[PDB]
Amino acid sequence: DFPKGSEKWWPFGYTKICNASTVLPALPKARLGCSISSKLLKLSEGTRDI
Image (cartoon, rainbow, N blue to C red; front, side, top):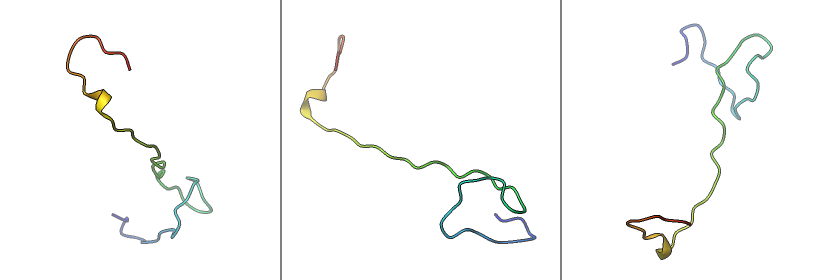
């Protein structure tokens, strides 16, 4: 929640914490990646090397 005194936010986020007048909590960084799916991964026991 915004503290009582003011409700203000940046329409496209922000990258620095200390700005012209105040200090904001950091935003989490973007989650990027991918995944692979195939039948060779059906492995139930023993030593497995992929």
